[PDB]
Length: 286
Ligand SMILES: COc1ccc(S(=O)(=O)N(CC(N)=O)c2ccc(N(CC(N)=O)S(=O)(=O)c3ccc(OC)cc3)c3ccccc23)cc1
Image (cartoon, rainbow, N blue to C red):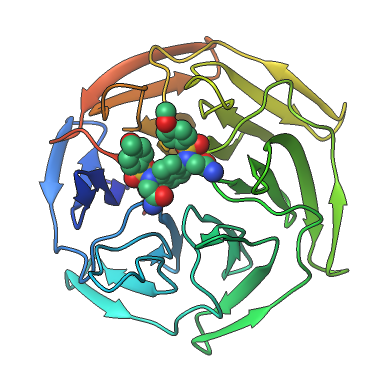
């Protein structure tokens, strides 16, 4: 009865409003308060025991479906709360937390492919922009390791990317790192045991099940055990020293499948399934 896995938003026929907490130990799902606005291709994160949903794409009927919204969920009260919106709409967004601050990375607004990045301070409820990335990335994967922010893969508006870059907060500058072996957009990126994992995604022709991690020491991307299902636009997070992937699109079907990665045995495996297949969710743990 400790920490739970929270899934918010997603897509099936349209942008979804579901918020659902999964309990890995007893294997159950709990339906929570809906998002005030349905959104797909959003990102989730956690700061001070609070759940945030960032950007994405809503179901607005006026032609403006790209979201610039930031929303806060309080588990203790089951209340969603609107926060200060970002400086620009960011669909297919990537998020990372450093020292209690949320970084919104890349994403898209219509034909605009953001290389820009902004930082949200919960203690001030403010968004301030920082140094833009070296590359424009939508469908980018973001993760944080030792107070450094990594932007991985994506789509620069012309080509799908295998390249990755690193953000140094104390210098406000970006620095390219070693590229992935695989071209990936809409991948699952996270930090587990001092490595940066990149799972699934879309190489431009197929959805992927291959998985590779990055080591700062050797500066190399090496493959690990592949997922049971190819999937892009998947939700990802860590729980109890294991990696969890949620939903996604395999090319024909919006997956309800949920797989778990054991780094000690280098094994993947389905452990449960969501209440309904869906892609482009945001996920966090608290
Ligand atoms: C037509 O089927 C789909 C597929 C995915 C969705 S989604 O609701 O999920 N969604 C919507 C969004 N808010 O943008 C997303 C769509 C596409 C994404 N990719 C683009 C990118 N730059 O990463 S993707 O690389 O992953 C991809 C590529 C080709 C595909 O067709 C075979 C399918 C997906 C999204 C990437 C991340 C989050 C949402 C995406 C909905 C319907």
